[PDB]
Amino acid sequence: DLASLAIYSFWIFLAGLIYYLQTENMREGYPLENEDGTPAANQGPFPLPKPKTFILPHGRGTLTVPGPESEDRPIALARTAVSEGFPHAPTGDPMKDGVGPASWVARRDLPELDGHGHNKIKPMKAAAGFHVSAGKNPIGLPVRGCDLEIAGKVVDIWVDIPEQMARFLEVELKDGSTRLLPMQMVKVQSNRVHVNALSSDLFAGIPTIKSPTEVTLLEEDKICGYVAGGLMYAAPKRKS
Amino acid sequence: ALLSFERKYRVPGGTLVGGNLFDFWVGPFYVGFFGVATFFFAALGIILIAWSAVLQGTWNPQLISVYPPALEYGLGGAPLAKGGLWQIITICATGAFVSWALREVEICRKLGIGYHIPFAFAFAILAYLTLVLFRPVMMGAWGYAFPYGIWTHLDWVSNTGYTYGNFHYNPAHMIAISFFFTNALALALHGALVLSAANPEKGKEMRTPDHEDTFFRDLVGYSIGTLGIHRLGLLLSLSAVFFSALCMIITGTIWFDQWVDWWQWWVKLPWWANIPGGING
Amino acid sequence: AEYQNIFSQVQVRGPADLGMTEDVNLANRSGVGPFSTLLGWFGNAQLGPIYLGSLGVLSLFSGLMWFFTIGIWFWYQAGWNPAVFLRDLFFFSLEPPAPEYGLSFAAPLKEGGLWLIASFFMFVAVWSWWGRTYLRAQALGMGKHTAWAFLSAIWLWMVLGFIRPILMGSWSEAVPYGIFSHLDWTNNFSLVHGNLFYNPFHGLSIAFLYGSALLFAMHGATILAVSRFGGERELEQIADRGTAAERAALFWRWTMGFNATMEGIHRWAIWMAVLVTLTGGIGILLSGTVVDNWYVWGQNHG
Ligand code: 2GO
Ligand code: 2GO
Ligand code: 2GO
Ligand code: 2GO
Ligand code: 2GO
Ligand SMILES: COC(C)(C)C/C=C/C(C)=C/C=C/C(C)=C/C=C/C(C)=C/C=C\C=C(C)\C=C\C=C(/C)CC/C=C(\C)CCC=C(C)C
Ligand SMILES: CCCCCCCCCCCC[N+](C)(C)[O-]
Ligand SMILES: CCCCCCCCCCCC[N+](C)(C)[O-]
Ligand SMILES: CCCCCCCCCCCC[N+](C)(C)[O-]
Ligand SMILES: [Fe+3]
């Protein structure tokens, strides 16, 4: 035996489980491509799974995966070698082009909705009655970049309503327009908010939102993309 | 071959050592300096383990076993066939692990993400070094470390354990185990929750984080949150391992008697040590 | 250096969240509890509301009943003295009836009847609680995953206190209520069966347990690394993949040469974890019923 039977059976089950698990995780990104975008030759031993359809709430439609994959966006890179597997150099300014660590996905250009169908992220001013409840309130702090120049000033916190947590700092620039900075990329200190990723002069370069009381999945990716890329690409102006 | 969204990310940069020299991939694997370093150590390591399996006289994988120098050798070297292989293999293993963590860092940098992963991996590495470096050095001999063999390492665990009686009574072991069990319970909960929301009853629309928060509060009167649960898992898991290494760093150094006995500090406290009745009086 | 996102830098509170309604009977939900600023550095600040309802009440009652049955017997073992009680707290033990009684409810209260009582109270408390994990999801429109996963835990526990004792013909085969004594049961069980290191399901259970710690570390560390692109927002990333999902996949692909999806990683997870108790349940169940000694069994690879 019984124990032998039980162990033998298990291993067989386990093998099937791994199969089901591996194929499940091939719902996105697959089939494999060559650097040119054509389907790569060897896909490996695992098949693609029969697709599945997720029903999005709030009439936002469906997603069905696996499905036809594409970037739905230009990619400012070019090869730097004559054979597969070497880096691809940015054709332009990688920050503005949204490549490398500055990369953003062409997600939906609407904002995530909470369970009730309302915008999930709001500026706190338009969010009632949300307020800072613990820790240093960043609102009104000057914002300093990795070049140690002030780049602006915090003029609200954007917050996740269902989850009640800070997601962005809305920051005013020398020209009086604003930008969202990912909460996770700023250090609130006693007397200032510090941003290591960007030098002061790249703040204006941050992607901007089309409407000033929401932010869409797409603009979030451009913004988080842009700022993270700062790490690699503002390496010239940093320093300390 | 590249995943459908991969090319935009495969830019130059992020390496720690040697600039663009090894800045390239090999299939899906990134290389870099530490890719090479890793390969080297692991290769040498495997060769040496296969050499040891020749000297031991077997090719069976359930029998191959590489033992540390015996207790008499102390912290000095030992002939290849009498411990020195294990010694070198150990150096190689550490080489491979640290290189693997550092290669992981280089990946992070090319990807503009956080460093949490190789930070977490570092905890496993330190558990390893406790067992084969810090404890054996503090006890005076390589011989106190475990042997590299599938079933022989289980003997080392079992022998080491019963040396202190039933090892359950080591309190750090207790705390460690609690974290392991809890972590596993949280893995099951998180996994199941996300999947219950993404894969609702037939026909219904995908639920939302609001449903997830609701489900927990409904069930237990609290919900940690989607940021929280990822903070938790990491902390449960690292803490389990932290307390693991802590429990063996102290066993055979600051405590060497029966773990069961250690507990008598509590029972023999002045304010009740002598009151008769119960299990101890 | 940078900010790591293990604790929050600023908390924000808004009005109490009373949760989604769906098909829940809001009559049975409580009102909100306090708000822990302390908790809020790490996770949510809001305590409550909790749904009760009658299955809840049953579990909660039965659970305390179980607990109290044990505590009464501990107090009693301490000769009603408070200081002895605290001193010997980890040593007290509610033992099951002696082999004499086999599977009968004949045993005296002082000699194992009490164990059976506290055990009855526990059996009720747990299963109802299970029905609760199913129902609370049903009422919300959600998958049954959580109740299925919980069943995996229930399995091992059932095997230990119920199925395996029955199959062995006595309640004395079962685990006692007591901190130190249950560790002793565990040690002894291994000895009397020839070392569980030789039981291959124990070996599997270990792999998964260690594996759960490895996975959740990776997963946990990964989400945090990509929290700067909103990774923690897993459901929306599932329904519309962002650079967060992508950078995640790619770190792992470049590191170990293959990777997951933002939904699939959770499938790995739910399995890695349930597999701990699953294998473990079988392993124990087989011990003493089919295999008397795992070393011996192992000598014949079966
Ligand atoms: C710290 C919490 C947790 C614990 C529970 C944990 C445990 C374990 C165990 C265990 C419980 O026993 C194992 C076996 C384990 C293994 C891994 N962890 Zn691990 N691990 C954890 C956490 C992490 C984290 C964040 C990460 C790993 C990563 C990794 C990776 C590391 C891969 C690596 O380092 O590659 C470089 C070296 C290679 C490929 C070969 C080395 C050859 C060497 C020189 C010769 C072998 C020497 C040994 C001492 C032989 C002993 C044999 C005997 C005991 C059977 C593997 C899958 C690594 C990874 O890639 O994950 C897929 C990674 O990023 N791990 N891990
Ligand atoms: C008879 C033995 C006795 C019994 C009483 C006992 C019981 C138990 C139970 C139980 C149910 O009764 C449990 C649950 C339990 C658990 C524990 N005990 Zn325990 N325990 C005992 C005795 C011991 C002993 C000697 C030890 C533990 C140790 C531990 C530990 C075991 C977990 C641990 O410490 O994990 C650390 C992980 C390491 C060291 C893995 C390192 C991986 C490395 C960095 C990377 C490896 C990469 C590979 C080589 C890659 C290969 C190629 C790849 C491509 C696949 C926990 C706290 C463990 C420890 O704390 O480690 C620091 C240890 O050394 N235990 N223990
Ligand atoms: C993959 C399997 C994994 C393993 C690792 C696992 C292990 C364990 C262990 C262990 C390692 O030994 C334990 C101890 C454990 C426990 C649990 N698991 Zn568990 N568990 C796992 C997995 C799961 C899963 C999916 C689930 C649980 C769920 C649960 C639940 C089961 C809940 C239950 O059965 O409750 C009934 C009885 C109760 C509540 C009374 C208890 C008395 C108590 C001591 C009194 C003190 C506090 C009172 C409640 C306050 C009352 C105040 C009054 C005045 C009103 C608990 C937290 C259960 C759950 O509810 O989780 C929050 C659930 O859904 N578990 N679990
Ligand atoms: C952690 C406490 C202690 C230490 C001494 C210990 C360490 C290690 C190391 C190390 C520090 O480097 C490794 C690599 C290791 C490996 C094992 N131990 Zn192990 N091991 C310990 C204790 C235990 C215990 C009780 C048990 C294992 C069992 C096992 C089993 C299962 C471990 C496991 O699943 O851990 C979680 C990791 C997962 C799921 C990733 C997959 C890792 C892969 C299967 C391990 C590769 C093992 C190779 C054969 C190692 C050599 C490769 C080299 C030649 C390049 C394997 C053989 C496992 C078993 O079934 O043993 C045959 C089991 O029951 N281990 N083990
Ligand atoms: C002398 C000890 C001996 C050695 C050989 C040994 C060693 C080890 C090591 C090591 C030496 O390093 C490790 C790492 C190890 C690990 C294990 N061994 Zn182990 N192991 C030993 C002996 C045993 C024994 C008897 C058993 C295990 C079992 C297992 C299994 C245990 C799997 C597990 O996670 O168990 C915990 C979960 C349980 C028990 C489920 C209970 C859930 C229940 C439904 C909820 C009840 C909740 C109450 C109502 C309380 C409410 C609380 C309130 C807050 C609401 C693990 C993997 C476990 C098992 O499955 O084994 C196959 C088991 O029964 N082990 N084990
Ligand atoms: C401060 O003091 C007061 C009085 C307030 C309360 C204090 C109480 C105390 C001190 C409580 C302490 C409790 C402790 C230490 C409990 C320890 C519990 C442990 C470690 C349990 C571990 C394992 C238990 C298992 C595996 C039990 C499994 C049981 C089952 C599967 C149920 C089987 C059911 C049976 C046998 C009954 C069948 C009967 C019928 C009628 C169907
Ligand atoms: C120090 C131990 C060296 C282990 C040898 C190589 C690892 C391969 C994994 C064992 C496979 C066993 N199998 C399936 C052949 O029976
Ligand atoms: C769900 C969270 C539960 C946390 C409990 C983890 C088990 C460890 C219990 C001992 C506590 C000791 N410690 C580490 C806090 O000092
Ligand atoms: C989610 C599945 C992950 C698979 C992990 C499998 C690890 C292999 C462990 C080998 C077990 C050894 N033994 C003696 C029990 O056969
Ligand atoms: Fe997750």
Image (cartoon, coloured by chain):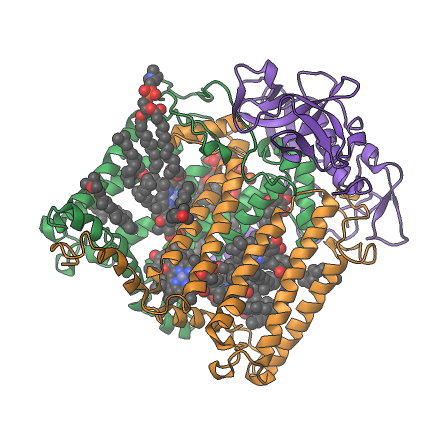
Q: Position of residue C69 (x, y in %)?
A: 18, 43
Please say if B254 is above or below A53. below
Residue C154 in view (yes/no): no
- When the figure is inspected, residue C195 is found, relative to residue A128, above or below; the finding is below
Quadrant (top left, top right, bottom left, bottom right) of the C terminus of chain C? bottom left
Instruction: Please tell me the colour of chain C.
Output: green
**B95 relative to C146 in the view: left or right:** right
From the rendered image, report the letter of the chain displayed in purple: A
Q: Give the color of chain B as drawn.
A: orange
Q: In the picture provided, is B161 more to the left or to the right than A196?
A: left
Q: Is residue A97 visible?
A: yes
Q: Is residue B17 above or below residue A187?
A: below
- Residue drawn at (58%, 45%), measured in percent from left and top? C221
Residue B61 at x, y percent in the picture: 55, 73
Q: Nearer the viewer, residue A196 or B106?
A: A196
- Is B13 on the left or on the right of C195, as rendered? right
Question: Which of the 4 image quarters holds residue B64?
Answer: bottom right
Q: Position of residue B201 (x, y in %)?
A: 49, 29
